[PDB]
Image 1 (cartoon, rainbow over the protein chains, first blue to last red):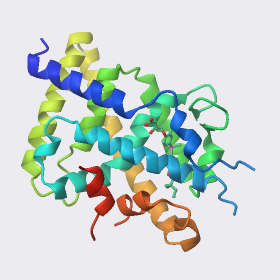
Image 2 (tube, chains in turn orange, green):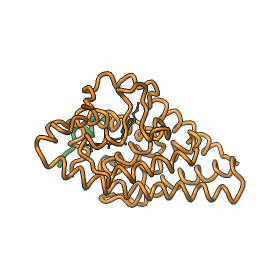
Image 3 (cartoon, protein in one colour):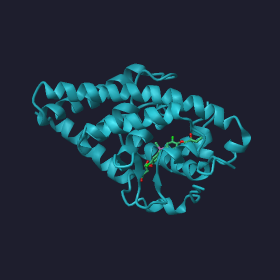
Length: 240
Length: 11
Ligand SMILES: CCC(O)(CC)COc1ccc([Si](C)(C)c2ccc(OC[C@@H](O)CCC(=O)O)c(Cl)c2)cc1Cl
C-alpha cells in the first residue's frame, strides 16, 4: 500500500538520519569535559552537546523532501522553534529506562536527572521531560516512524512567524500521509489509530516541553555569567 | 535580528 513516492520519502529520511546521527558518540570527546562534582558545573559540556545537536538537526532538516522549497525566513523560523523539540526527540535513541538516563557510550557521557540540573534547569522541566522519554520509549517506534515524526515536527504550519503556512502544511501533509500509510502497513486496526494518536500526542507534549525550556532558558541566558558559557550557535538559534 | 551562523549552516 506504500506508494513509490512514500517509499522514496522514507528512504530519504532514513538516509538523512543515518548521516546526522552517530551512534558511536565519538564527537563527544571534543566537547568541554563534563564536571559532576560555579554550581552549574555541567553547563559547559551540555552547552556544547546542544550546540552539536542543533547542527545535526539543521543537516537533517535540509534533507527533508520539500524543505528547500521554502524561503530562507521560513526555514529559519521552523528550525528556531523546532530545534529544542527535535533534540528531545532524537535523544530518545540514547535514553535507557534502567536508570532513567541518556547513555551515550561512557559513564562520562551518561547524563541523568542531576546532570540536567547542573545545567540550570529545575524539575518543572526535567520531570515532564523524563515522563516524555519513557512514554516515547514505550511506543517502540521503528526507525521509519522515528524519522517521520522528526520531519513532521520540523515542518509544522502552526509556528509563530511562518510566512507560507499553506506550503508548510502541504509538505507536512505528504509526510503525515506517508506516516499513516506506514503504520497501516505494519499494524492492523484499531492499533494503527492508537499508535498514530499517541504519536501526535507526543508532538503536543513537545510544545509544552518547548514552552517550559524556553521559559527557563530565558531566565538562565539573561545572566551574563551563564550565557558566557554557551556557544555562539546556541545564542543565535535559541535567542529571540 | 540576523542569523548568519544559521544561514551558513543552511547552505
Ligand atoms: C545549553 C542549553 C540549556 O538550556 C542550558 C541553558 C540546556 O539544554 C539542554 C540540556 C540537556 C539536554 Si538532553 C534532552 C539531556 C540531550 C541533548 C542532546 C543529546 O545528544 C543526542 C544527539 O542529539 C547527538 C547524537 C548525534 O547527533 O550524533 C542527548 Cl543524548 C541528550 C537538552 C537540552 Cl536542550
